[PDB]
Image: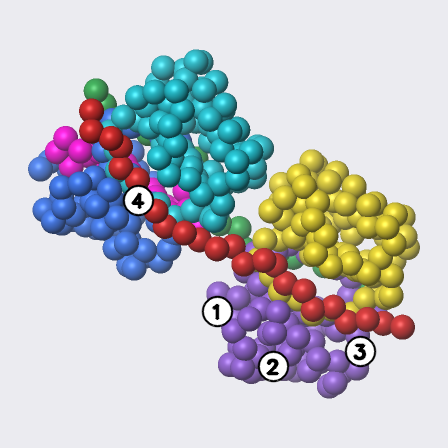
Chain colours: A green, B red, C yellow, D purple, E cyan, F blue
Amino acid sequence: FMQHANVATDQVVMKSVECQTEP
Amino acid sequence: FMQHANVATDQVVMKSVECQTEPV
Amino acid sequence: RKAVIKNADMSDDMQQDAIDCATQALEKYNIEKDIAAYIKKEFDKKYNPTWHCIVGRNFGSYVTHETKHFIYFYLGQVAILLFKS
Amino acid sequence: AVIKNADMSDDMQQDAIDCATQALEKYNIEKDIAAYIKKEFDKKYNPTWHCIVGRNFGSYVTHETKHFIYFYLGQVAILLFKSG
Amino acid sequence: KAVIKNADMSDDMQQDAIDCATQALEKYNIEKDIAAYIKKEFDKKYNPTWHCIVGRNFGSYVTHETKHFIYFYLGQVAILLFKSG
Amino acid sequence: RKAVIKNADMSDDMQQDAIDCATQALEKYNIEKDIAAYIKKEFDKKYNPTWHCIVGRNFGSYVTHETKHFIYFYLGQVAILLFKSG
């Protein structure tokens, strides 16, 4: 029998963020 | 017939750069 | 995005179908693991088992494929390896 | 050595790791590392093997039973399986 | 008025960067929102991952993928846009 | 010379290290690009590539960073953005 494999490299969780300097 | 394949991803070249805003 | 064929041992029609199928996959998924699953499964139905697919930005490979059943190409920044064995 | 997924005998699992350790010592390029491992397993355990070496990729493959391994060696991920 | 101080990028992308930035300044007043618009647009158009800085007074040291960097002014406002990851 | 952390996704030790490194940077350099270069280079060495640093008094930003590798803070009147991506 043949088996299916679904593997991938480790995922580095990413975050997006806003920054604004004060007046 | 079976063929062999030897391929690899392109190297992603990184560059560093300085930036400075103009004097106001 | 833009399709760029680096290496191919495959018919012109099949090559284009691989690109089209991969184009659909990127529109459907963002995860490389899921994108590869779609492409492999699609080619198993259309052109019979057994296909294998690798999707990513950084990898090297050494594989054996059936003649006229191999393609290696980019869609934007993503590399796609697709072959039958 | 870190085994992420495996459907393979313990002796072969150990042999794949050993072969990959040798590969890393000889080569620095992923393309060469994969080539060494594939050829080695084709010689030892008959065709047809396939090998993927890299840090960023996703995959969906079909393998013969008891002939599949996916693991890390340091910072490098290695996929090895038999199909055909 | 667009003034390019430094650039490692294709001419099409550069022009697209300026247009995209031009739209942003017309729509938003807060620099962070201007940067958000430009970043999000380039992530969709030219794949992740982009980063954008918008302001009149800052200095920076960043690492970018080759042919994916631009630094320019739109009037008195400086815009840094680059891809890394 | 008062350190004020506005936003952070980073370990306390790294955060404290970011402040210390920036304090050294301000003591050594006066040009904002040089201050940023010092901090970036130092964090690339200590905590692996790839870091990016923004130093200034007036800017807004939208960036993407790896988890637990982001800090945005002031040292006195100067704003410093430091994050890892790639």
- The chain containing the residue under callout 2 comes to D
Name the residue rendered at 70%, 56% in the picture: C6
Name the residue rendered at 63%, 63% in the picture: B8
Task: Inspect the magenta stretch and tell me whether residue F70 lies in it.
Answer: yes
Q: Are marks 3 and 2 in contact (CB under 8 Å)?
A: no
User: Could you say whether the residue bearing mark 3 is in a helix, strand or loop?
Assistant: loop
Is tag 3's residue or tag 2's residue first in the polypeptide sequence? 2
- The chain containing the residue under callout 4 comes to B
- The stretch of residues the image draws in magenta is F65-86
Q: Which residue is mark 3?
A: D47
Q: Which residue is mark 4?
A: B18
Real-space Cα distance between discs 2 and 1? 15 Å
Residue type at numbered disc 4: Glu
Real-space Cα distance between discs 4 and 1? 33 Å
The answer to whether any part of residue B16 appears in the image is yes
Q: Is residue E32 left or right of residue C42?
A: left
Mark seen at residue D74: 1
Real-space Cα distance between discs 3 and 2? 16 Å
Is tag 1's residue or tag 3's residue first in the polypeptide sequence? 3
Mark seen at residue D19: 2
Dot 4, crowdedness within 10 Å: few (<14), some or many (≥20)? some
Name the residue rendered at 9%, 37% in the picture: F1
- The chain containing the residue under callout 3 comes to D
